[PDB]
Every structure is written in C-alpha cells, then in structure tokens.
Amino acid sequence: SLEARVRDGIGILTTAASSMLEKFSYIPEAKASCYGQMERPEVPMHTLHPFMVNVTWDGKDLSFTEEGYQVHPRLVVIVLNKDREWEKVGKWENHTLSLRH
Amino acid sequence: AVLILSEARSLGLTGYDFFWIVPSLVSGNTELIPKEFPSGLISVSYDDWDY
Amino acid sequence: AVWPRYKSFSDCEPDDNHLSIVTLEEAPFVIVEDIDPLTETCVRNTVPCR
Amino acid sequence: ILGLQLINGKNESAHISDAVGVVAQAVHELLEKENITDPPRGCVGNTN
Amino acid sequence: FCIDLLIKLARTMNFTYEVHLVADGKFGTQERVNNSNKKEWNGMMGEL
Amino acid sequence: LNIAVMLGHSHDVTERELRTLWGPEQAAGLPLDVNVVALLMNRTDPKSLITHVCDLMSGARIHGLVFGDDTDQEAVAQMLDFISSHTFVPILGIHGGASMIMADKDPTSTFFQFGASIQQQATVMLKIMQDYDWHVFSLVTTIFPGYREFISFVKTTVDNSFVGWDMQNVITLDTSFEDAKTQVQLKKIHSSVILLYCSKDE
Amino acid sequence: KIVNIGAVLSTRKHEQMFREAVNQANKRHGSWKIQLNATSVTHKPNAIQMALSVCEDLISSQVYAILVSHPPTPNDHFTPTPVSYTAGFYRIPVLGLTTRMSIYSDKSIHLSFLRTVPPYSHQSSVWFEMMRVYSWNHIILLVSD
C-alpha cells in the first residue's frame, strides 16, 4: 500500500544519509539554485550516490542495479474476471511462483 | 460485384493466389471493364467472338 | 495447362513462395503414371507434373 | 594521415532550406486525410 | 589415415600445419555450464 | 534533512491523514532527524514539473524527493531523469507513470524506480506458461521501443531449455492497423497462446 | 488553414534566412488551404531556462514540428537534449540539422528525433567500401568507448 511505499522510500533515503554521515561529516546541503546564471558544476561528483544502493531496511532488502531496476522485485500475476477487476492469481517469491489456481 | 471486389481489395484476399470466379452476368458487357476488377478473373460466357 | 500466375492489381507483394522445378524420369526414384479414371484428379500420394 | 570530411558540414542555410521544403511536402501530403487534430495549445493545461 | 589425407591436402593446397592433439578428449557436445543458466560447446569442438 | 513527498489524487486521497509517514515518532532511532514536507498535485506537464521542483528547491532545500503520480504518460520518467541530471537532487518515484521502466539512464543520473526489468517479466511469463502446459504460442510485437530486446530474450530462453517449446511464428506487426498488410499476417496465428507486447493504446 | 513551423536557430541572420526560406516555400504550393506561418527562438545557455523558453515561446503557438541546430559559439556542452525531450513528450516530431553524436541515433530514448546528416557510422561504412578497392584484408580495430 502507498503508505508502505512512502515509508520505505523515506527509510532508504535516511539510511543512505546516515551511511554517508558515518563515512564522513561533510553532508552537503544543496546547490545555489536550479536555474539562473549558474553554469559551473557544484557537486564534487554527485555528493551522495554510491551509498544509495545495496541497502536494507531491517528485514526486506532492496538494492538498485546499475541500470536503475531492482534485483529482488515483488512482481505479481493478475487476471480479469466477470466483474471487470484485476483480482489476483498467485504471486512471485524468492525464485518460486506458487500459483493459487 | 464491383462494390464487393473493391471492398475486398482493401483486405488481404486479393493477392497473387486468391483466384476469383464469376458468372456471365457479372461480366455481361465485355467492353465495359470497371476499375475494381482484378487482373485474374475467370468468367464463363456465351461466345460472341466467333459464331 | 498451368495457370500463368497473373498480376493481382498493379502493385502487390511479389511472390517468393513459388518456384519452378525440373525432373527427369528414372526407375525407382521418379515414376510417371497416367491419370486415374475415377476421381479424374491425380491419386492421393502423387504430384501433378507437366 | 588519411582522414575524412563531410562536404556540406556547417552550411546551415542549405540544410534549413531543404528541411523547410521537406516539411512543406509532408504537410501537403498529410493535410488531405480523413482525421486531423490540432496540436496542444500549450505545455501547461493537458497531459495527452 | 587422417594424417595422410592432411598431407595430400597440404601438398595440393599451399599451407603449413602445426598439428596439436586435443586437450579434453571428448568429441564435442553442447552442454549447460555448471552453476549457471547458459550452455556452451565442450570437447574437441570447443577449440574450433 | 528536508525530504519532500509529492503524490496526488490516488487511492490514498486522505491528504490530511497522509501526514503520518514519519510525521509521528514512528521508529526514531536513526540519527539526523529529518523534516518531511508534503504537497498535492493534480496535473502533470513539463513546465509545471519544472516550476514545482525548482520552487521547492529554491525554498526548503531538499536532499531528495519522492515522486509518484496518477497518470499513464510514459515520458514523465524521462522528464524526471532530466530534472535530476541538471539539479543533483536525488529524486526517485514509486507509483504511477514515474515508475514504468522503458530505457536506461545516464550514468550521472540519480533517479531510481520501484520497478522490474523486461527480462524479469519475461522470465515470469515463461514460468507461468510452463506450469499449465501451454508450450506452443506465437509473438505479436509492435514497433514500440525496446521490442528487439524482448524478442531476442524470448528466443534465447526458448532455445536454452529442455521442456520442448514450439515457437509457431514471430510477427513484427507494423503500420496502421486498418490496411491489408496488418490483416494478411494477423491471420496466420493458428496457435492458442499469444504474447502481445505494445503500449496501452496500440 | 494556418500552420506554424518553429525553429531553434543560432543567430538573427539564420532567423532571417529561415523566414525568407519559408516565405519562398509558400510560393510553390499556395493554392489556398495552407498558409504556413513561422516563428523564431534563439539558443540560450543553461538547460532549465531553455526548456521553459521552448515550452512557452513555441507550444503557445500550436507548432507542427520544431527545427533544432547546433549552438554556434560553445562546444557540445549545450547539446539539443532539452528540446528533444520536451517535444517528444507530446510526440511532436523535431528535426535536427548538424548534431552528430550517435546518442540520438537510437529510438529507445528519443522516440521522435530525425536528423538530416549521417551521424558517424557511415564513416565506417565508407571505410569498408574503400577497403576492398584498396585491397586490404587483415585489419585491427582500435577505438574509444
């Protein structure tokens, strides 16, 4: 559910921030402005980035691959019915399907 | 006939191998060929070339 | 004796699944027979050759 | 050293003229069609 | 037999040979590599 | 930090009650307590997205944004990548058009999505085919970008197992779906399972 | 009845040339129906201001296609990416003129971007074509990545 999604996002962002703070106490705040007369680069490379992947949240893990995907998603397989609504049939798991019907 | 053949042209079934066949009254005037007939129609008719 | 494959209208896909084939009679390999009286088409396990 | 070079290159005038010609040809071809709808009125206002 | 055939072929053609026996021993087959999800050619066909 | 959360007009239409993710103490054990600022957006467009994100940046300096919308437009992901690349703001979407994956991202980008690649979806599809004994089928893919990777992956997976699949034919169906060309090669699908791949309207 | 063809050119002289060219093109097939007006925007630095400017100054006039070109003064640091993204949001086709980088050559990202110059690989094509004419077979390939 959406609340779980936003909670997980806040968690991963905070964990990345804590990891970067533990590495060093630099913690850059932000840039001067999104637009305007600014043209020179600001971030050293991208401030924080390599600590945003291979992170966990005390239980379920989620690490973003180099191309932007996940590595352990939560795909499910769904099907319409006579009431015109995707209900559910089975799900995915570690590497197993385990269909219901 | 011309309407149906034109409508079937705007569909798959007027290719190289889709041989059509029509009676005499579909081709009853000889020298009044419409545009929409294919170039492979086969039609039987009372002869008017000889006789 | 064979349908000359007339052009469809003016511009259709040129045929690429029709191709002529030659053959010469020999004793156990290719045998040429006549046409069956009943069911005046060729027999079931046979092909029509001009 | 055996190099290479495009003959026209930075000749933006000829490219501009030819692009305008091609777009004019395309719009003349297209505007005689069964269904035609105008482009969006602005960036802000719709997401279609 | 094959050595004589190769000698005749090399004499008729124009090349030189450096015959080396196979390392594995198997004639050659397609097989799925262990601890993976792909497959490859093993045996003498592998060196091809 | 000043993480900003931005959704709009979804099943979670509470809005006022949406201020509950990290709003209360929850699990306040990690150091560097953060401040969460919410917003509600109905419509999405390039200029509007640019203005909203830039205005948020100019005000409460965000160290990362969490997006998520309701519309089905596929290019909002590209617009978000473009925003993140030239602003150094770690944006990442969750639900909606800002999540569907279609193409890779520039190495300098910092935009991540809660999604799954085409390859994982293809693997699950083949697995669900194999369980119910439907190993005979045919592909029907349009000219939508990324179709070549899908075709190649399915072909390799079929040619790398032991079950005994039988790919009847691969159709690259293209051009307007009214003409004779669409109908001639859509009539040859004599199998019983079809594996369409296209956008929603197509 | 009336249509517009905007462009993102380099300098004012190119704008005058574009206006003269479109006026001349209006002379060939002008049997009523089409009027084919024109608009004008010059390159700008940065990227965000560029996207805002293209949105307002072009899509406020119901363009049918945009025409982009390489920046005159700077190097490739100002590639026409923002215009391509903004135009491809609505699937309005955009035409490039002198941008050869082989990154726009694929349709996966830039769905609607067709140019009028061969990007770089046709150099390899002509290399191979001349290779047989000069009769060399064994070659090596050294290239960046």
Image (spheres, grey):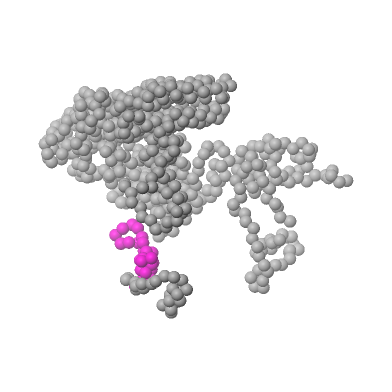
Q: Residue furthest front?
A: D1
- Is E40 one of the magenta-colored residues? yes
User: What is the quadrant of residue G54 in the picture?
Assistant: top left
Residue C49 vs residue D18, the one in the foreground: D18
**Magenta-highlighted residues:** E25-48
Residue B9 vs residue G9, the one in the foreground: G9
Tell me where residue F1 appears, x and y as whole percent.
17, 31
Q: Residue furthest right?
A: B51
Q: Residue at x 70, y 67 (%)?
A: C32
Q: In this image, A66 relative to D10: left or right?
A: left
Q: Is residue D15 visible?
A: yes
Q: Residue at x 38, y 45 (%)?
A: D3
Tell me where residue C49 appears, x and y as whole percent.
69, 61
Residue F191 vs residue G93, the one in the foreground: G93
Q: Is residue F150 above or below residue D16?
A: below
Tell me where residue C27 appears, x and y as whole percent.
67, 73
User: What is the quadrant of residue E24 in the picture?
Assistant: bottom left
Q: Is residue A84 visible?
A: no
User: What is the quadrant of residue B39 in the picture?
Assistant: top right
Q: Is residue E41 above or below residue A48?
A: below
Q: In this image, G100 relative to C4: left or right?
A: left
- Is C7 one of the magenta-colored residues? no
Q: Residue at x 36, y 73 (%)?
A: E19
Tell me where residue C5 appears, x and y as whole percent.
68, 50
Q: Residue at x 63, y 39 (%)?
A: B9
Q: In this image, A38 relative to G72: left or right?
A: left
Residue A19 vs residue G119, the one in the foreground: G119
Q: In this image, F50 relative to D32: left or right?
A: left
